[PDB]
């Protein structure tokens, strides 16, 4: 029932009790581990509301108080009559913060308690949504001194009146198929880009064209809006030693801001809830630039360094990969935009992990995602056993709106 | 019921049915994934199901399932179990068993090679001296003057659990570690305790950074005995870098033959508790883990110093820079001496090919992502992007506790 996790580098052993308060299903069974898989009513809502309010009132040291019981009856009275309910502001801030605290795939959670929450539940139209989003972006960006934030639109009602940001991130580069055969810009965003064009976007058709927002309010057909270019902080990519690096013409945006996830608090579902923090360096240098399925620039860079690409055993990909990632961290720092390197991020997460074990009895963590996509074993997280389980409140994936929403 | 795995780089989708033939548990539940946890006497009753299961497998593969000779072998194993409470594998079943344990080893990236295993049968062995000789011959055959060949040597099975054959070494060739009174270690820090054991069994320690440990060998549940591997048999490679000439002055070498000697081979219910096996190295095993782990030789600083990197902020990626150079050096040194080695790009790529082939012909390939993805440069290898299903097939290799923790000393 109780479980041990061992760090194999420090021999430190921790005991997890938090997993018994775990609720949703993992995908795994006694017969099969699915750890590496990316995606494995009134009667339903009240248990969910109760479990959430119980943890809320317990966190404020008021479990079994008058204010507790009374709130429990009030939600019950709202559920029985309205078939949903409304979170108080204080409950909403707690819910969002804990959804982040519980995100087993996030290395950045040491910061969980500093989330700035923007309550956009009074929003009704896409122009309304656009305004809230620009305020989010500007607030979070802070001229390069980035701050964590989430903006929460109105919750699901009947599932015919959903608020959705169709973009997967608020700031992303477009993807275009060429008559040539290959791809200009980000090949990850090719489909969405075509949905932007088919909705009426004028695409400049270059390598780094910031996509327009596609916003859906109250189940309506979604609407295009360009983000004020003055709000999109971007960094030109140079290397501190290699002069030729700048003429690759690389740039990235400072603000990572996930906008396609669904926030669940006390059985209530918030389908538009964009959140943003700041980058770990490898997210851009390793994944965005070097993934065969992304900008895939390793070939071009290795060529500029004059490495031996005759054989894989010269480790030329690995050499180029390090430099690319050195260039990313350097560029961001030189422009004073917050960024964390993978050594720093993982060390902080080990500190966070040990904080959560002593202060909560555990910390759900997905090793496959926490271990950075380069230099895994030289980061302390590699040697750290982790337990993965699903707690609520949480962020969940949701189907893309275009596969679903009717026109 | 059929399960799909997706490669997120290529969008290739594969369908697994083999997991239906899975028996043992994984450690996971619907409520918890233990996918990153390192370690999560039998009765007649259970033994015949296991035998039957295995012989059904064996006879299926040779296309003799249900034949007179398959039936006769069931009846004969049946009888042997009730008459003696155990049974004996035929030669052909042993081979086959051993190849399939490797094949089913979900943490091993080297399985494309599974069908080429040299099996040595050492089931006539009765003494520690007998074991030394079998192991020497193993090492010589597998080494093949640098042109490494996979091999397994199999000693007699467990009977009552009181008469076990064990190789107390975790690997047949490994370097000593010696903790000093000042708190530092000389040599491989992983081996400190096994070293102490060898010392107190009578090994007179040379006490250098690279002393090849003696073999400590238990036969027939007896106390084990010391033996030096003949040095002419221990192929070693001095480590140098193709461009950095100060690299050899670091004084590093490594042995060429990785040979795991602490695992338990389970086939058709029988337990072979000494089955050392050996292959060749993937370069990252030496350059990333053996040299650069903080708990191992820990040379990153010393190398980054000599490279004059900016070491005053981790954000210079000095560790990542030094790590790549050391790994370049390891592959360079092995190749120049014509000792078999494989780089991680080449090994992960071959494994992906192995894996797809296994889905087509076998209906699955159990694989453990945490272990298969290399400890550097993860996402630039094709495995990082491969979803994988992990489950337990038999025959298999299993962990077993360290013999010094369980052994009843006789004197
Ligand atoms: C503050 C700095 C932050 C850092 C350094 C960070 C880091 C990361 C990283 C590296 C990943 C894996 C990303 C990938 O490779 O695609 C991740 C995933 C995730 N992060 Fe954090 N994050 C931060 C802020 C936040 C915030 C503010 C939230 C929510 C409030 C959050 C919630 C999540 C969630 C839900 C995932 C999983 C997404 C998925 O499953 O695809 N993060 N994070
Ligand atoms: C021939 C070349 C081979 C290569 C390149 C190879 C590669 C590897 C690597 C890199 C690992 C885990 C890395 C680590 O040590 O942490 C591993 C694990 C393993 N290998 Fe292979 N291997 C090879 C041959 C074999 C052979 C001959 C066998 C047995 C017949 C075998 C069975 C296993 C087993 C059972 C594990 C799991 C070990 C554990 O769970 O700790 N391998 N292999
Ligand atoms: C808030 C925040 C801060 C930060 N530093 N980092 C993040 C990572 C985002 C989250 N989620 C994707 C990451 N961004 C990477 C963009 N690629 C898509 C990821 C993906 C791939 C395959 C399947 C799938 F469903 C999603 C968020
Ligand atoms: C035959 C062969 C060839 C090859 N290239 N490679 C191998 C890897 C061996 C097998 N298995 C690990 C490697 N041997 C190293 C010892 N393992 C330390 C990590 C560890 C820590 C704690 C518990 C545990 F189970 C393992 C074998
Ligand atoms: C905690 C974690 O599972 C452990 O450190 C594992 C991770 N992956 C590994 N993978 C390999 N190949 N070898 C190892 O020793 C480990 N260590
Ligand atoms: C197949 C595998 O699950 C997949 O490629 C995962 C592995 N780990 C990851 N880890 C992070 N942080 N981000 C990712 O997108 C992925 N992709
Ligand atoms: Zn699992």
Image (spheres, coloured by chain):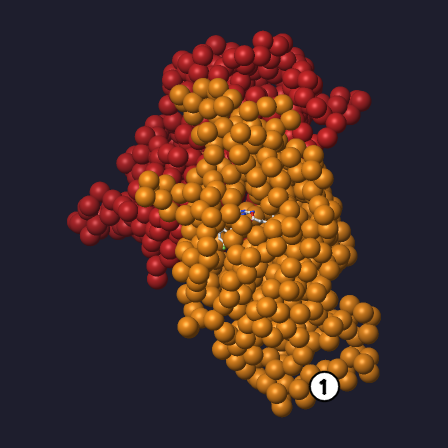
Chain colours: A orange, B red
The answer to whether B393 is drawn above or below residue B219 in the figure is below
Side of B315 where B79 appears, left or right: left
Q: Kindly identify the residue that appears in the image at 44 percent across and 16 percent down.
A: B335
Q: Quadrant of residue A10?
A: top right
Q: Kindly identify the residue that appears in the image at 57 percent across and 84 percent down.
A: A43
Q: Position of residue A230 (x, y in %)?
A: 64, 50
Q: Kindly identify the residue that appears in the image at 27 percent across and 46 percent down.
A: B361
Quarter holding the N terminus of chain B? bottom left
Evaluate whether residue A95 shows in this view: yes
Q: Kindly identify the residue that appears in the image at 20 percent across and 45 percent down.
A: B63
Side of B171 where B43 appears, left or right: left
SS state under label 1: helix
Residue closer to the observer: B48 or B360:
B360
Q: Position of residue B404 (x, y in %)?
A: 62, 34
Evaluate whether residue B393 shows in this view: no
The answer to whether A293 is drawn above or below residue B114 in the figure is below
The answer to whether A202 is drawn above or below residue B169 in the figure is below
Number of other residues with Cα within 10 Å of mark 1, as a class: few under 14, some 14 to 19, many 20 or more:
few
Residue on which disc 1 sits: A74
Quarter holding the C terminus of chain B? top right
Q: Position of residue B375 (x, y in %)?
A: 55, 35
């Amino acid at each position: 029932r109780f479980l041990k996790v061992k760090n194999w580098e420090t021999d430190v052993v921790l005991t997890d009790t938090l997993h018994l308060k775990s609720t949703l299903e993992t995908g795994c069974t006694e017969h099969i581990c699915m750890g590496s898989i990316v995606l494995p009513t009134k009667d339903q809502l009240f248990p969910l509301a109760k479990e959430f309010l119980d943890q809320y009132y317990s966190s404020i040291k008021r479990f079994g108080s008058k204010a507790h019981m009374d709130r429990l009856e009030e939600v019950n009275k709202e559920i029985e009559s309205t078939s949903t309910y409304q979170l108080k502001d204080t409950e909403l801030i707690y819910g969002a913060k804990h959804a982040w605290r519980n995100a087993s795939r996030c290395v950045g959670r040491i910061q969980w308690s500093k989330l700035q929450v923007f309550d956009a539940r009074d929003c009704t139209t896409a122009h309304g949504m656009f305004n809230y989003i620009c305020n989010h972006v500007k607030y979070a960006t802070n001229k390069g001194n980035l701050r964590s934030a989430i903006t929460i639109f109105p919750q699901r009602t009947d599932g015919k009146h959903d608020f959705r940001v169709w973009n997967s991130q608020l700031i992303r580069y477009a993807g275009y198929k060429q008559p040539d055969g290959s791809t200009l810009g980000d090949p990850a965003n090719v489909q969405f880009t075509e949905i932007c064009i088919q909705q009426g976007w004028k695409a400049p058709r270059g390598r780094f064209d910031v996509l327009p927002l596609l916003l859906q309010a109250n189940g309506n057909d979604p609407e295009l809006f360009q983000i004020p270019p003055e709000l999109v902080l971007e960094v030109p990519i140079r290397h501190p030693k290699f002069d030729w690096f700048k003429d690759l013409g690389l740039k990235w945006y400072g603000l990572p801001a996930v906008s396609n996830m669904l926030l669940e608090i006390g059985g209530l579902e918030f389908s538009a809830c964009p959140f943003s923090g700041w980058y770990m360096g490898t997210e851009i240098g390793v994944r965005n630039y070097c993934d065969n399925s992304r900008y895939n620039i390793l070939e071009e860079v290795a060529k500029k360094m004059d490495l031996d690409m005759r054989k894989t055993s010269s480790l030329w990909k690995d050499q180029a990969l390090v430099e690319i990632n050195i260039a990313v961290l350097y560029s961001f720092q030189s422009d004073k935009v917050t960024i964390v390197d993978h050594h720093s991020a993982t060390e902080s997460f080990i500190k966070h992990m040990e904080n959560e074990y002593r202060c909560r009895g555990g910390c759900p963590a997905d090793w496959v995602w926490i271990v950075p996509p380069m230099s895994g074993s030289i980061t302390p997280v590699f040697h750290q056993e982790m337990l993965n389980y699903r707690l609520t409140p949480s962020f969940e994936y949701q189907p893309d709106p275009w596969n679903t929403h009717v026109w």
